[PDB]
Image (tube, coloured by chain):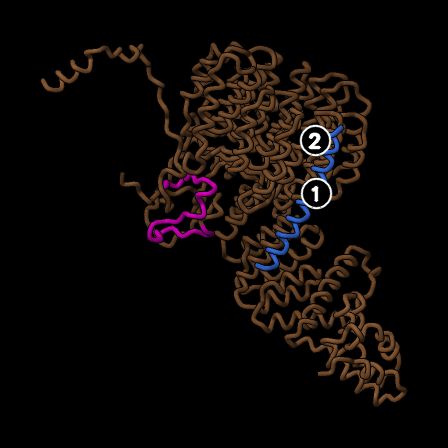
Amino acid sequence: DLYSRYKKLQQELEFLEVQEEYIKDEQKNLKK
Amino acid sequence: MITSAAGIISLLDEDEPQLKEFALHKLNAVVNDFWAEISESVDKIEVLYEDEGFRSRQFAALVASKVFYHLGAFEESLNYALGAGDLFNVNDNSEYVETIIAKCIDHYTKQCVENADLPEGEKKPIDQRLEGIVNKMFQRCLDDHKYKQAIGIALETRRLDVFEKTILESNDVPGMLAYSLKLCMSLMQNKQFRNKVLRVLVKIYMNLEKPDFINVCQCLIFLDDPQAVSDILEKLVKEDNLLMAYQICFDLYESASQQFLSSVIQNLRTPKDQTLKMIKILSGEMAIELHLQFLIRNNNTDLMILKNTKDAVRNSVCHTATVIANSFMHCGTTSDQFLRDNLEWLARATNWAKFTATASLGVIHKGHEKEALQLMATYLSAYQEGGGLYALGLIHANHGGDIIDYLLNQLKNASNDIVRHGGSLGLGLAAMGTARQDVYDLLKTNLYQDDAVTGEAAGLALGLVMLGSKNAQAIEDMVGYAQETQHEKILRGLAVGIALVMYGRMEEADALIESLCRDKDPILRRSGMYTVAMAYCGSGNNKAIRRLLHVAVSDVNDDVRRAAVESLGFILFRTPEQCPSVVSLLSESYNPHVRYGAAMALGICCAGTGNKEAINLLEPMTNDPVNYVRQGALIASALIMIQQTEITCPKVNQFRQLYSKVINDKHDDVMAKFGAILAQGILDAGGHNVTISLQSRTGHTHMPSVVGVLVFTQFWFWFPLSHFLSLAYTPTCVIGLNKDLKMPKVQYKSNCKPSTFAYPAPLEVPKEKEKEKVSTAVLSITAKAKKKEKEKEEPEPNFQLLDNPARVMPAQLKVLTMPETCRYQPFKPLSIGGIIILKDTSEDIEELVEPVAAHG
């Protein structure tokens, strides 16, 4: 239970940070 | 109290190794408060530890670890805690102990993960005392009757021996095995470690008192070990256990790929009736026959909606759209009633529309393998002949075999380029995954020309044939021809072909992905996006997601942006809730191509899932001012809501009304209408009997389904490929088979209301509305006249019973059973579905079920 939840949170963190990277790049292109 | 440790620290400076140790003891006793002072004097304790010591080497380590922990330098605290040795006393409710334990566990996990990938001998040694601390934690967790999550710590630390020991020497071995398999299939990513863990799991399974052969075969499918599965089957048949083998072979066909099935069949080849029918099961004759029989028996198709679309159609685009939608709604049903009724409509087609119509015929007759060849000969220019080839290939899906020689021969003896295109598509479909050298070389020869129509099919069929093989020769030849050619259509064909070739290879595809992405040809960059998708299919790989998301906004070619978004959906299909988070922002993009890619990515990801946020995102996109964004949104909504009822999703009726409205409209764009017509076809695909799921019932990725979805998405460039979605149609059937491999009349029992999984009701004609007088005018005395006239004058059943061919919706398997445990007992729960070998204990007449004629 706890290990599965920990892995879920780790994957969510990785997914959210990659999403933020994408939003930063898209914002830059939108400014251009 | 004491208020100052200065005296105790000063005791250390002396030269007496009898005073020093008492100083250390008091210092440890008081480190709970005076770490601030002791920190500046730690260096003295450091040097005192770094000598013979005389109990100083023992206690100073613990003191320095404690003071460093209080200070904040855990990296240096760990070294001294380890040097302490036996003075750590792991067994105590101390916060310092807990924190150092956590830090040591994290350090060990990091070290193991880092050094595992390195060579066998080139490994940086671990500290033995650190290993001892980790093992002490393992043993403490075991002693706490906390068997679970010791498996998790073992998984993180990458050491198996503890994992095996704790999962064996524990209660509820079945439950722990189920948890371990869930972890091994879902969360962990490293493929080599996954294979090692699965090897341990299968060893445990076999050494169990009663081996779980079904889970063993699942793990062996994951490991790609046909020799081992063949040996398991050989042992299982040598020992008298036939139902086990029946269900094992059924699941093996339903999950494993064609190459694996062929290899296991060859191993078996290397009474004999048992072996022969095992080979037949693995080849899949009975699987496809049972699926076709299921669909024909339950062919509850609706014709009035298709009639309305036909009536509303004006343009050739909408005509071919209706043809394809009919194909989808009749896929696997072998019933061409609409096409045999509207011979004038069907005959108003021309050029590639005839190709598409014949392909629709083939899709309708999907799985109808027995009368093939002669059936197409009866059904009947160059376009018609090529369409017949492609339709016959579609009928002979991934499971081809015997007809490969016929396709090879006639594509050799084909003259028209249209016929060559059709034959190449059919041969690629028939040989999908076989990787036959002769077929590949013939397709190479057919590709080695300058002609778009032939080259596109030749390249796509090359990809289908080499699928997964990772053939270096194939990649080299296809990339070289793509670079050296001059026809963008051939380029598109080769792009999809390379994408398919580099399928299922997680990290072995990265070199080719980088090459294609850095390539300057926009079609080859699109090929790189598709290669990313196919390689990291259904893995949620964050590296691939990052690459695709980067290319979706950095690249200049809108085609490549759209392909990147589609690939993103292909990657994320395994976690449907996850994708809407990605695609909500992409859907609100000023780039219409990226918006369409977002819609199609949502469709692929949530295909046959009926998610709610995906539909919420699609609906506004369904209402857009751009032309093709609407088509993409409609098709994605159909993909998502395929086989969904009003109660299950309270928007399906809304989208049905939307499709009807857009079809029956004056200004609605041609491509919007095309998308709506397709959407209807997919939504009612297979006569409400088939759903689209890229993964098998047991979680294995469904290669035919993913290939079909990808090639269908590649209809933006070529309509005839739109029929490839047929491969993505899976019958939502639970079929019970007894020992004789014949379907007996069983009664399945589902405990749910008969409206959350029922077929959409026929809507009948909308009826004629007469002319209405408008609100007869009220005058001054009308109310008085009305007053004068006034004076003068459910059960909602909670039960569901299904005959043996049981169209059970994917959500409608968790809740499914039989009445009072009838004569038939399931070999495996009625939750996985598929084909179940119902064991029987009562002997009676046992009437079978009739093999309905294949006409509809």
Counting the numbered discs, the total is 2
Distance CA(mark 2)–CA(mark 1): 31 Å
* Residue B241 seen: yes
Tell me which chain appears brown.
B
Mark 2: amino acid: Gly
Q: Is mark 1 on a helix, strand or loop?
A: helix
Q: Is mark 2 on a helix, strand or loop?
A: helix
Chain assignment, label 1: A
Q: Residue A18 carries which label?
A: 1
Q: Residue at x 75, y 69 (%)?
A: B69
Q: Is residue B847 above or below residue B58?
A: above
Co-location on one chain, circles 2 and 1: no
Which hue belongs to chain A? blue
Mark 2 — residue?
Answer: B463
Magenta stretch: give its range.
Answer: B802-829
Q: Residue at x 87, y 80 (%)?
A: B48
Write down the quadrant of residue B127 in the picture. Answer: bottom right
Q: Quadrant of the C terminus of chain B?
A: top left
Circles 2 and 1: CB distance less than 8 Å? no
> Residue B268 at x, y = what percent?
61, 48
